[PDB]
Amino acid sequence: TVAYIAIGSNLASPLEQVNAALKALGDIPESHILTVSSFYRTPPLGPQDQPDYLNAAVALETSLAPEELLNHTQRIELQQGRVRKAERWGPRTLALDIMLFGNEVINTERLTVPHYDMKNRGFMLWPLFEIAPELVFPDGEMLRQILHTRAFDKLNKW
Ligand SMILES: [Cl-]
Image (cartoon, rainbow, N blue to C red; front, side, top):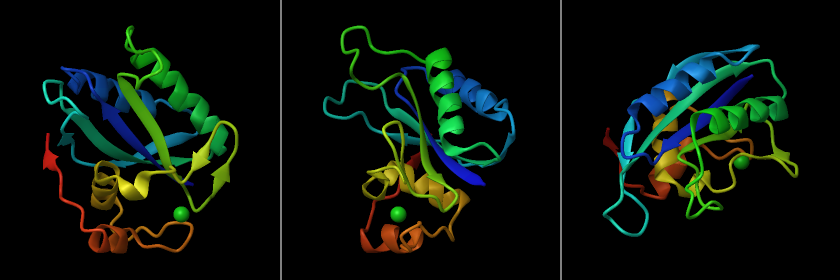
């Protein structure tokens, strides 16, 4: 099954973090990376005196069950990133999100796929569109139609 995974880092110096994350994704058993999007840049949320986000999408071929893949993305998040000590409930430094898992729809305590908000997020949709322009969501909606109708601004490359 092809899983699509979003990578997002908010480190002031995110490159090695993202490259290490890609290495780790490629080390996941029963899986291999099919392709990786370009690296994109998005602005911080709220105050602008914060670091930009580095965003990318990864297509991963896997024979793991969705929850098993989640185990690995969670592990990689723990091993390669951290919480902010002042805002521990907040976002981690490295985020790996399973955007799509084949054509599967999943709604469990641990896992919701497709990612619940991805259709509203250009920073997820554009890198995905670079590596899977013909993608159709499980509900039948076309990625091309979402980007076109909703008129997202494009993202700058990292
Ligand atoms: Cl869907």
